[PDB]
Amino acid sequence: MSLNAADAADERSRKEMDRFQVERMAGQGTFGTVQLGKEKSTGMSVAIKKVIQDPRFRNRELQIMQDLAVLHHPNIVQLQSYFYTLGERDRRDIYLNVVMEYVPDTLHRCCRNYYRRQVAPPPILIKVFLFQLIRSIGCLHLPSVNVCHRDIKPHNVLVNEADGTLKLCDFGSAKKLSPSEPNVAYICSRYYRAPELIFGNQHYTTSVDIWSVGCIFAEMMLGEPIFRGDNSAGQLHEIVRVLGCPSREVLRKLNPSHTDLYNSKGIPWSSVFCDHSLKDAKEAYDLLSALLQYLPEDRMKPYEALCHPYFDELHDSATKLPNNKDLPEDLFRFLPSEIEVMSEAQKAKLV
Ligand SMILES: Cc1ncc(-c2ccnc(Nc3ccc(S(C)(=O)=O)cc3)n2)n1C(C)C
Ligand SMILES: C[As](C)(=O)[O-]
């Protein structure tokens, strides 16, 4: 219940730890370990995450979480605390711990519960989740924030199915990018990696996140990842197999040397998803194609995508989640920093 003061690496950390009680383990994996706890002062459920930092790469979880904590964005986790603990199996190891609010599920697990029981997720849940995921990157990509997550995947998109809410987390791989400065192209889970990253480009933009989001939209409607390659070239083959071979000019723009594959005509979305009951499939598929453009600049930007006709029914107070609950109150609650950068047409539609 109490966190063990003896595991604090220092006084500051012992004092932060005393704010929280541990209820139980929530999940463990390659990233580290997430415990469900409570803030003792408010009762609030928290995720206490013990961060495992791969020394081959730059981990920016704490610094990016601190920059985002100023915004209070309804679709991004809010840092509550950070502190350092000694390792369980070897006390010479010290770990960063970040505390944020707890969200009960991942989008991966929520979708997998439907597919495993032979049901596709309800269309209105896919739609409300997508709206929120796009809003989360909208916020990250603002000029005032300039954060590229670079590892968006169903496993770090958090959801509460009961109230239709969604939050983005897991910012260890995130970075503010500049066209002047180079980056590591091998970031992101291979299945969600944009073509410019498959090509090993060291200069790339926040549009890599848009690709990842499109990939997730497809996976929510398919039940498995849409582009499943065994390697970088395998990944391009799978993309080209589904979307069709782009022109040589497009391939030359993406290939850094600017100077090689089957000429697939691509599969229509209708044959990929086989969902004849989806009443607005045409809109859904238009949106998907607008996110999954080969050239980064051609991809639909988040605030334009929020105004896409696929999302029209989210404006109707009569629209309900599958359990008959109202849509989340915060869907159309925008931050001043978001509103002040919108076009007049986007403000009219969304605010
Ligand atoms: C990587 C990461 N960084 C922060 C979180 C995070 C943040 C807030 N809430 C939760 N809740 C949660 C955790 C694990 C599971 S599980 C393993 O049973 O699927 C289900 C819900 N987690 N996480 C998550 C994505 C592990
Ligand atoms: C090595 As890097 C792209 O995380 O600054």
Image: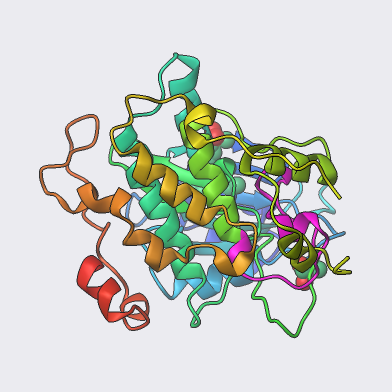
Query: Which x, y percent locates residue 112?
Result: 50, 25
Left or right of 303, for residue 317: left
Total number of numbered discs in the rendering: 0
Query: Which x, y percent locates residue 329?
Result: 21, 54
Is 272 magenta? The answer is no
Left or right of 314, for residue 249: right
The answer to which of 203 and 298 lies nearer the viewer is: 298
Report the magenta residues as a range: 185-208
**Quadrant housing the C terminus:** bottom left
The answer to which of 226 and 138 lies nearer the viewer is: 226
Residue 41 shows in this picture: yes
The colour scheme used to paint the residues is: rainbow
Query: Which x, y percent locates residue 314?
Result: 23, 49
Snapshot quadrant of residue 118 = top left
Magenta region, main secondary structure: loop
Point 48% across, 43% down: residue: 217
User: Which quadrant of the figure shows ligand 2?
Assistant: bottom right
Point 55% across, 41% down: residue: 154
Left or right of 89, for residue 115: left
In this view, 21 is above or below 320:
below
Residue lying furthest left in this view? 318
Point 62% across, 65% down: residue: 296
In this view, 303 is above or below 115:
below
Point 47% across, 45% down: residue: 158
Left or right of 59, for residue 230: right
Snapshot quadrant of residue 9 = bottom right
The answer to which of 237 and 144 lies nearer the viewer is: 237
Query: Which x, y percent locates residue 330?
Result: 26, 58
Residue 102 shows in this picture: no
